[PDB]
Length: 63
DNA sequence: GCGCGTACGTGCGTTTAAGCGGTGCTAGAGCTGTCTACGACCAATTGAGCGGCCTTCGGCACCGGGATTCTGATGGGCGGCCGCGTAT
Image (cartoon, rainbow, N blue to C red; front, side, top):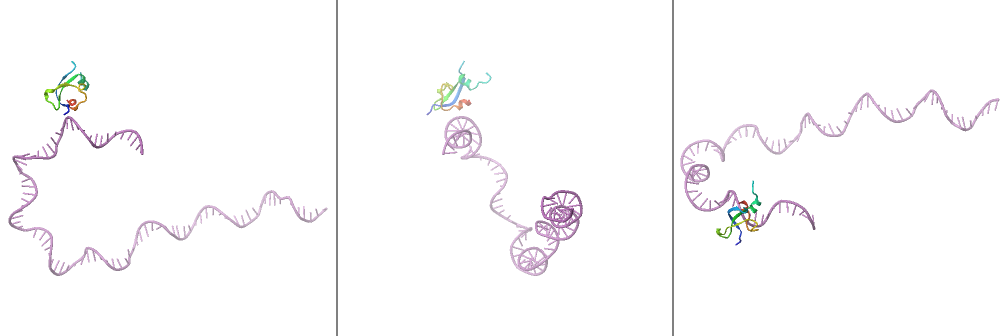
């Protein structure tokens, strides 16, 4: 019944180097996240500072 | 008792491999069947084994005889006693 992160769909950049770290992935890339308990038609391009603390976060870290 | 520290329990997510029932294959247990070697049994003779009884040399620790070293009464000779004592 909770509105958490299920799987990851697509990924792109948000703001239009040798190795981008997690900070560059936060303030430089947006990711299409599929939410649990919901169809795949409600995929939204979200990051970390736009959703806050949500259920399930290690999957997007590994991806 | 108390206080500091941290490691181990509880959670979620990721991940890895047990358990399920499906088939195939043949090895190794179990059965089976004939022979005969090896163990039980009975016999008769013999000495290893047990009770009965007292053995001898070597090793621990107490011992043995003879020369030699240290302590004690002995003794003439050089000195000191100053105080009673006989002679003029």
